[PDB]
Image: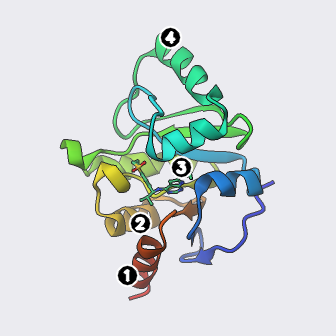
Amino acid sequence: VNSFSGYLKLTDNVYIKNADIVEEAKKVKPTVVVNAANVYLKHGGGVAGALNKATNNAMQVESDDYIATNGPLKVGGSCVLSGHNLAKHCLHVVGPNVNKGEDIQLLKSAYENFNQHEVLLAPLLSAGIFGADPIHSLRVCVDTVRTNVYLAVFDKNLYDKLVSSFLE
Ligand SMILES: CCNC(=O)c1cc2c(N[C@H](c3ccc4c(c3)S(=O)(=O)CCC4)C(C)C)ncnc2[nH]1
């Protein structure tokens, strides 16, 4: 039903909230939840692990079946699969892991996938252990995504830093 609440409106189409994406998916029941995936869809930790555990491992079983038939994704690519109990669909998006030396230019390619969905609940791509500068990731989102994106950032200090930087 996409009933998002408690978000700050940064631009005409980008919103942000200090929240756990799993709890937001349970509260909002969005049409699309974005997963910060890796190319072989192994959802063991971070955001992907949090989403998979909230589906009681249904997301991992479906992803394994996808990988068996189709092989891995490319960095910057995406895949629509079921959202299980969290959303109607899960858009698995692979942003670059700059801590492992992947190309930061592909973060624009990763956000470009959001433009195929009129409204999405999403994490901040390539942040956390993927090592991208989180302020840069928020700027790429703002400049690339035209559809309505609701970013959940589960860290108060990071959220406050992103907001303060954007409002300069
Ligand atoms: C209690 C269960 N929930 C969680 O653990 C949880 C964690 C979490 C979250 N983490 C951010 C984040 C954003 C992007 C990426 C990562 C981490 S990663 O997994 O380190 C690598 C892939 C890219 C941090 C930057 C704050 N953002 C929103 N909702 C969340 N929920």
Q: Toward the viewer: 138 or 40? A: 40
Residue at x-position 39% and y-position 35%: 38
First in sequence: mark 1 or mark 4? Answer: 4
Residue at x-position 62% and y-position 47%: 33
Residue 11 in picture, x, y percent from top left: 54, 76
**Structural distance between the alpha carbons of marks 2 and 1:** 10 Å
State if disc 4 and disc 2 touch (CB < 8 Å). Answer: no
Considering only vertical position in the picture, is 139 above or below 161? above
Question: Which one is in front in this view, the residue at disc 4 or the one at disc 3?
Answer: 4
State if disc 1 and disc 2 touch (CB < 8 Å). Answer: yes
First in sequence: mark 2 or mark 4? Answer: 4
Q: Quadrant of residue 162?
A: bottom left
**Structural distance between the alpha carbons of marks 3 and 1:** 23 Å
**Structural distance between the alpha carbons of marks 2 and 3:** 14 Å
Give the amino acid at mark 3. Answer: Phe
Question: Quick one: SS at disc 1?
Answer: helix
First in sequence: mark 2 or mark 3? Answer: 3
Residue 46 in picture, x, y percent from top left: 45, 46
Question: Quick one: SS at disc 4?
Answer: helix
Q: How would you rate the neighbour count of disc 1 (Cα within 10 Å): few for under 14, some for 14-19, many for 20 or more?
A: few
Q: Where is mark 2, residue-wise? A: 138
Residue 145 in picture, x, y percent from top left: 50, 59
Q: Toward the viewer: 104 or 12? A: 104
Q: Where is mark 3, residue-wise? A: 114
